[PDB]
Amino acid sequence: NIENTIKSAYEESLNNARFGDKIEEIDAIQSTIKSAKNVTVATSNEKKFKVVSDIISRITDANISMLEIPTNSADLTRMPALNKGLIAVDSSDADLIITRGRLGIPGSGSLLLIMDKKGRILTGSVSPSSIIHKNPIDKTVELELITALERIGIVVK
Amino acid sequence: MNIENTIKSAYEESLNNARFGDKIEEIDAIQSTIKSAKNVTVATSNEKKFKVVSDIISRITDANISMLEIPTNSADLTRMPALNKGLIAVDSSDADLIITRGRLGIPGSGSLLLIMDKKGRILTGSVSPSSIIHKNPIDKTVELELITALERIGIVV
């Protein structure tokens, strides 16, 4: 479980022995994602929700839901994607939260995060502002999610 | 013109949920901030990584470029290590621009590179997989991360 991998990693960083990631840490992240029973997507856009739900449904046996609470208030924070995720974390009992929003300030493009029930960040990906790169939003969200999963060893084809 | 302005303007739209897309001004402010930096801190004391970053950054700004001598290992016991490493540089120096790279989230979540300004605001960034997932020379990983982070706000290296 990630509590365990986190506790062990914390103890070793202090030892100045943190010399790379471990397969156990990846395995724990994969397990957390695949075993999720209730997944919340921090969006109210039905088109983005469908893109996310269709992918996540292939790797979980979960109830997947949109977040009912609007999340635009997070756009007045330093890390909007993150804070949208925390709204879902703090107001529901989702096992897994998928959030997408601005990375940082206006113009900084998008960040997608997969977070666990405590708001811990498991994986993520970024995409450019639409000013910089024109792309259908559904293809953008799809690539973000597939990328975030691939980089912790989950391949969806 | 500047990031305070674009931020104030974007926040005002967001209060209405009337924020529908990014603006060219926002990208312009980010580029101007990067290009006009007087002092850049790279949040590392590894000279090989510093050279990779410096060689790229020196071509887009006339800033003094410096390493961070304060070790950053402590940030690995935080929820967002790359971010908190960056904030060490923000809070302990008078850098205009901070380039930081470190863990995205929990152990196993791979790496996040961020470009932050003098207040710790996030201008752009990029992610790379854990070495467990993708084996790769560290300096070419950092090079790709930095180029990607620059290109997504319209700076071509």
Image: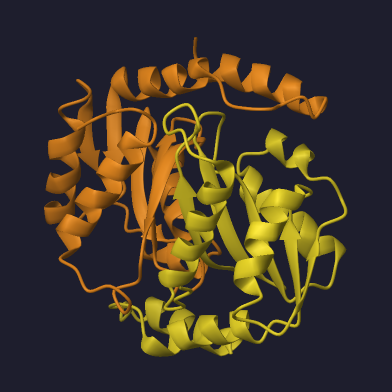
Chain colours: A yellow, B orange
Position of residue A15 measured from the top left corner of the image (x, y, whole percent)? 35, 81
Position of residue A145 measured from the top left corner of the image (x, y, whole percent)? 53, 61
Q: Is residue A16 above or below residue B146?
A: below
Question: In the displayed structure, does residue A135 sit left or right of residue B22?
Answer: left
Position of residue B16 measured from the top left corner of the image (x, y, whole percent)? 83, 25
Tell me how many marks there are: 0
Position of residue A144 measured from the top left corner of the image (x, y, whole percent)? 50, 55
Q: Is residue A136 above or below residue A36?
A: above
Viewer-proximal residue among A128 and A78? A128
Question: In the displayed structure, does residue A1 sit left or right of residue B72?
Answer: right
Residue A106: image quadrant is top right
Q: Residue at x 58, y 59 (%)?
A: A113
Q: Quadrant of the N terminus of chain A?
A: bottom right
Viewer-proximal residue among B96 and A86? A86
Residue B8: image quadrant is top right
Question: In the displayed structure, does residue B150 sit left or right of residue A136?
Answer: left
Q: Residue at x 69, y 82 (%)?
A: A36
Asked if one can make out residue B46 in the rendered structure from this viewpoint, the answer is no
Q: Quadrant of the C terminus of chain A?
A: bottom left
Question: In the displayed structure, does residue A93 sit left or right of residue A156?
Answer: right
Asked if one can make out residue A148 in the rendered structure from this viewpoint, the answer is yes
Q: Residue at x 77, y 64 (%)?
A: A89
Q: Residue at x 38, y 87 (%)?
A: A23
